[PDB]
Image 1 (spheres, rainbow, N blue to C red):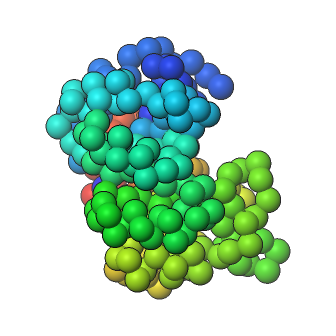
Image 2: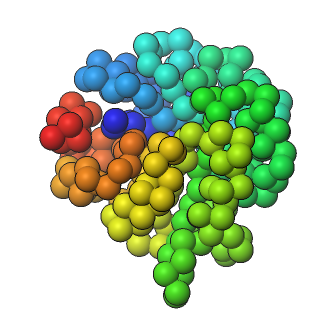
Amino acid sequence: MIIPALDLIGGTVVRQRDYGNDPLPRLQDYAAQGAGVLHLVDLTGAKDPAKRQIPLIKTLVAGVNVPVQVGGGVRTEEDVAALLKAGVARVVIGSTAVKSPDVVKGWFERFGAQALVLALDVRIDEHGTKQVAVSGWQENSGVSLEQLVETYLPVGLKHVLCTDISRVSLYEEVCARYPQIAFQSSGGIGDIDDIAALRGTGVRGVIVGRALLEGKFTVKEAIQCWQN
């Protein structure tokens, strides 16, 4: 499916570039065009978990009729629980999934794999290895995408979000290798042709953010393309 995305700072939709303070009508129109899932990044919370935008997230989730996956500096069991309590369908786990796998495996056991998405940044190194990194501005963490995925398979891993931060063959490879996992792709979507390029790869979800904000195409057009 297409997964439209918004990044939020203090109630503001951002890319830094300001897109106004109307995230709810934006999300509602995404849903209205047929989106089955939405993606939110809480940039405020990612900078200070004490300022996690729980009240706003509550309102946004209550305001649409589709599951929303939400991430942004989720570090603790308590972060996960508070997001789910606010009505989030799935919590997106980034750096913590690389940093403390045994802890996060406990979270799978507690919350269920349907409630968790692992967001992994990947850069292809000199040798062609898919290296995991916790962010675009930090060095590789010393573990490959395959190795980290295989760490979580025994607790029923089902959802992985994969962002290529080095830049299709990448997604073809990992999706084929782990057909029991629903991979999402993130980044690199500049126009409708980019969505088409992902169609035969095995990727289950396509995160689309900035291209929607820039008016390159609509959610409806993205879905029609995806569905061929």
